Length: 173
Length: 76
Ligand SMILES: [Zn+2]
Ligand SMILES: [Zn+2]
Ligand SMILES: [Zn+2]
Ligand SMILES: [Zn+2]
Ligand SMILES: [Zn+2]
Image 1 (tube, rainbow over the protein chains, first blue to last red):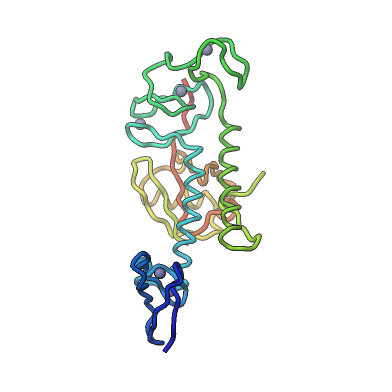
Image 2: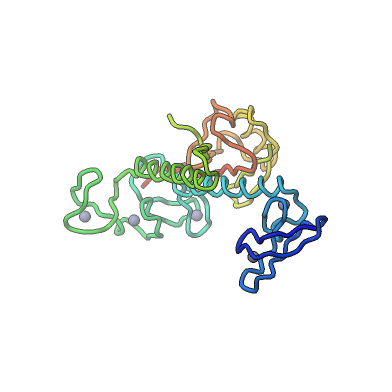
């Protein structure tokens, strides 16, 4: 016999010492949680406490790995194929024929989408607001990708408690 | 490990790999399952291009990570 407090709202309930499922009596909580690891009961079926902890961790790490890949990849609006520009201007032609602006990723029909005025590298255009035809976004994208890895590093420090953190993507140069 | 690879065709396949397998080994295992020649494969993980020289552990590719096959296109 043991008295247990809900891991969320702290409402108390009497539980048999051989029951692992905690069902909170609080009408405004109602959360069903595991009693050994405080994990959510629905997400817990068929898994041990360790297998659930690993499952949520992999879910998080892969979410950041794909968040970094998403910043680098251009997805064709028609066929969904991922594109990367090796060189050239910012007008992309996917193998399906559809065209897109490599900067803002919108679907376009031709060169009329782009600003072609005299324009210094990474400088605003004093005569339009269209996308630069020649600007290379590789450095800016690599910065955004690193911001994701750093923000994922700091959100790990909040959950773990200590200053323990493991890098998600590949290392630095 | 067990990792996922997303084809150009949209299908996601699964591979049995080890962190010591080089990228060339992975491109081979992709060819055995989908018939995609390795010289045609452009692999990208966590936003970074994969090169034939290094291994999966060098790119910090862990369990259930996804490698994306992409088209490396020239602008125009
Ligand atoms: Zn509760
Ligand atoms: Zn549990
Ligand atoms: Zn396409
Ligand atoms: Zn644009
Ligand atoms: Zn302009």
